[PDB]
Image: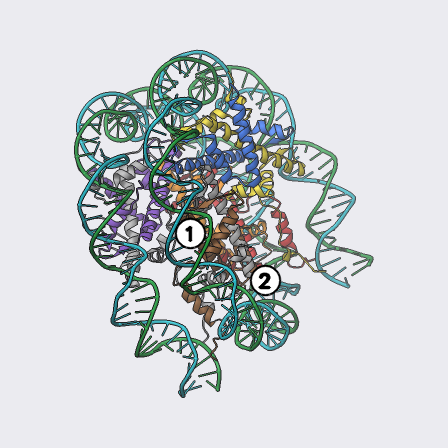
Chain colours: C yellow, D purple, E blue, F orange, H brown, I red, J green, K cyan
Amino acid sequence: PGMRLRSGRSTGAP
Amino acid sequence: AKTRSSRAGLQFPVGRVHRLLRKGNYAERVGAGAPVYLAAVLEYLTAEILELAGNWERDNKKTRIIPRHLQLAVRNDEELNKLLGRVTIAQGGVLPNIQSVLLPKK
Amino acid sequence: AKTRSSRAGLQFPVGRVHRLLRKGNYAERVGAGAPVYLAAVLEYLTAEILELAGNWERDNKKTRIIPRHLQLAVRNDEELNKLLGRVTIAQGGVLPNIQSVLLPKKT
Amino acid sequence: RKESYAIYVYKVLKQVHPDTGISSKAMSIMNSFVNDVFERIAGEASRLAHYNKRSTITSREIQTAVRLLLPGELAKHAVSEGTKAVTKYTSAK
Amino acid sequence: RKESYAIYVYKVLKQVHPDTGISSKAMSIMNSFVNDVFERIAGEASRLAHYNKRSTITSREIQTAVRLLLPGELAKHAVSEGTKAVTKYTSAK
Amino acid sequence: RKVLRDNIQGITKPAIRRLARRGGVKRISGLIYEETRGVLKVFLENVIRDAVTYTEHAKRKTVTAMDVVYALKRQGRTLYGFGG
Amino acid sequence: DNIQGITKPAIRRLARRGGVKRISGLIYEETRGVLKVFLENVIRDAVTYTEHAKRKTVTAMDVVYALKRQGRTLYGFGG
Amino acid sequence: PHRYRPGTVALREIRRYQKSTELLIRKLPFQRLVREIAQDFKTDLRFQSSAVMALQEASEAYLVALFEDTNLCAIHAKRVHIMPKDIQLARRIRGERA
Amino acid sequence: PHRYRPGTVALREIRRYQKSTELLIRKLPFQRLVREIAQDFKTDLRFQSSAVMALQEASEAYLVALFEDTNLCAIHAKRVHIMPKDIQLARRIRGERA
DNA sequence: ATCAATATCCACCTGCAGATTCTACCAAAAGTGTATTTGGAAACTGCTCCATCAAAAGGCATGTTCAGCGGAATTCCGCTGAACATGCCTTTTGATGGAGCAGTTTCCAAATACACTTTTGGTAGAATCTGCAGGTGGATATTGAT
DNA sequence: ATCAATATCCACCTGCAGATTCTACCAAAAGTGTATTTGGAAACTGCTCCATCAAAAGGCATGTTCAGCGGAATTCCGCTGAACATGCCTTTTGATGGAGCAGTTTCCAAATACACTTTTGGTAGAATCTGCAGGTGGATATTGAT
């Protein structure tokens, strides 16, 4: 799980 | 052989980032954690922008991101806009905006 | 033994400047011309601003240059004013200047 | 040759909008974007170390540099992500 | 020990105006002045060298730097003083 | 010792007029003073925020004049006279 | 001249993109003057990079660089 | 004889141009003006087609933004007309003038 | 019973303050504002006397330079009375707003 | 146009903080001098891609006309500057205790320095593929005259 | 409220410039293993200078009163820019020798890197020096009432 964007979404996946 | 970006769990080139720091005359020495921390920060801000630019892409019913979208993404976002407040995105237009004192009448 | 400075005909220290360019991390190496040339441009500029300040001092019937003299000198010279356009000289005040519309009368 | 962050920019794109493409012109802007920020952060990093008479930059600098360069929330998220990439990177082998 | 340009500013002061002094606050401004321009020129020089994939800062980089940074006249005279100084220095041995 | 509050009011009406004077201002509206303190407060918050960031990075508990000087230069307000 | 080649209709379009609804006739001349001062400051620096690199061709980077130090960074023509 | 009242079309164009991204100055005239101005810094020069485009892009964005601030000054003085003095006051505050 | 017309003393003041270079804000007061603002950003902080001086110096040179722009903005609107809208139009153009 | 009321200008005066004047130690500069390494100018050359010529392309220049905007004139309400009385709190001088910045010696985790091996991101000539810009059309929203 | 001249919109269509996927060779990286080196935290602690409380007085903030005149609302008209249609000249689009920007090779002046040897800019501190800040008083404005 990658990074958390301000919007709440994340990279997920590697 | 496993790459550092993998160890750091990043998309960005941790090696490259690291290579650029040293060959950039920023300091005598470069800690091993610097490029890692940095690569992350660059990847993260990159995601942040594509994220919003992508949104602008669908708003205008388009599947491919072009400069306009990037402009719309950055200027429509108080923080990214401040970050790039003295940057000009070539082929990025301007946000639609007409000073109220200048429209119609009743 | 001769200071590289005297060799170049300069008052400013060529060695110190050569030194600081290294420690400053501006490039891998630093040719010997660099410090000579830079120390000069620096020495030339201080002479330029001191010439003007000293005059400002004189104009004010003062023997000792102070910040205000430095400000008057700089802000009264198109070129220096620009070179320092985003610099603030502590204790330097501003140039006497009042917009016309603000003055009394007409005729 | 001429390196660019293009592929990585692209890999990150698909992580967020898997069905969205990107024009070359746009890619060119993202690269200018990355190179820019890189430079700003690296530069600030550099200064900090010089101010404090330090020879090594080192994730401390990169971080303080982020705090100094990135706006509000944008910086909050940035600092964690970085602090995370360095931990994950460290806790391995 | 804390270094300064104070004596060199002073020498020069006595050259242009033999009977004029300078208060410490004034001298301090002067000290900031030099370090300031010192930094800016070195910086421009730094970047010029990189843009051109060179690892050395020669008098030449410094010169172009002085041209990009100083306004019209000041630059023409700075370059003069510079070229002249290097030349004399060279033929010094 | 003592809780610090409402000091932006230490930026008295008099002090603010003087400033507009050195600035060439002849007539001042009654609403200027509050607007001014608000503007001064943002300026001080940004400059101090940056200065203190330097301090913490140096692991000191004392904000130095260099901290402020480095802070000012970041914001494009380079100051001469304090070691900077 | 060539500066007059930057026509009224173009300055009108530019102005429009910036929200301008009414344009005083004396504007066009004033605009060209401003645009000239702009190009002079940028080109001057850009060419100074060109010369420093012993070239006879101003490059996009030569421009991207001038612009950057003019404090007007441009994304799109080279990192 | 249909006939839009003054300001209706200008308002139309404002809508239009704030939507698109294309440069609004004709390329060749611009291309001439650039070379002409550069010819005073170095004789016999060549410009990559990209350097010109970058240069034009920087300029239009500059002017456009300068019109925005100019409009602000005009509106400030309770007008709806950008005048030379408006551009002047704006460039002045910007630090480009004095 | 003497009495100067409104504006006479004001003009006297501009000429006066434009002649001196001493700080116009009370020192002790300014120091607290700084210690307050600073304190809400981080606790148990200390200040070198000279650091407070630097902040005052920066601040006043800032506020003064801002007032000139404001003053121009009012005059632009054909007033001699600076108002908040003036300070605001200036900061917007300057790029502190925008 | 004179007149009284005050502020401004100015040369003189002098106690004093701040600057100039040594004395003396000296660590850190800075310079002198073989040794080793090498960045980059110099000459040579192929391949872009840039300046140029030319025919297809479509936007700018010109003049009539008049709507509506800017600026002059007028007017009045009330806000803001000048003047004054009252007294608070900042500023100045000082002495103090101790936080905390700063110097110094120690010393190991971490970085630089190769050496070698593995991979990978960039160039490419080639084939293949697709988001979407214009274009048509027919519906309907907008503006403006009546 | 009533058309009607137009602009704007939306659904649908498809050609292709531009994005994509491909096979492929490869210098340049990026990773990896070994040896050497040092930058900077740690512990100790000298001593700068910061927070503070003390005390006093007068500089200057505060609050008020009062009315001059600036701002802003308003009416108004002279005129300047906006809209528009007529006429075509300049810019745009595509094809082509060739001037240079780059890729490779070369080798020499110049830049390390290291060792001492020498000179100097900082500084500590007791010390005499001196420009001028701020007090003074009178001569010359400058200002506002008449």
Mark 2: few, some, or many residues within 10 Å (few <14, many ≥20)?
few
Describe residue D24's horizontal placement relative to residue J28 as left or right: left
- Helix, strand or loop status at disc 1: helix
Q: Position of residue J43 (x, y in %)?
A: 41, 29
Which residue occupies the foreground of this view, I6 or C91? C91
Query: Which residue type does callout 2 highlight?
Result: Lys
Query: Which residue type does callout 1 highlight?
Result: Met
- Helix, strand or loop status at disc 2: loop
Disc number placed over residue I78 in the picture, else none: 2
Which residue occupies the foreground of this view, C100 or E45? E45
What residue did someone put label 1 on? Answer: H53
Which residue occupies the foreground of this view, J64 or J34? J64
Residue at mark 1 shares a chain with residue at mark 2: no
Residue D25 visible (yes or no)? yes
Q: Residue at x 62, y 28 (%)?
A: E15
Q: Quadrant of the N terminus of chain I?
A: bottom right
Q: Is residue I4 above or below residue D52?
A: below
Q: Position of residue E28 (x, y in %)?
A: 53, 34
Q: Position of residue F35 (x, y in %)?
A: 48, 56
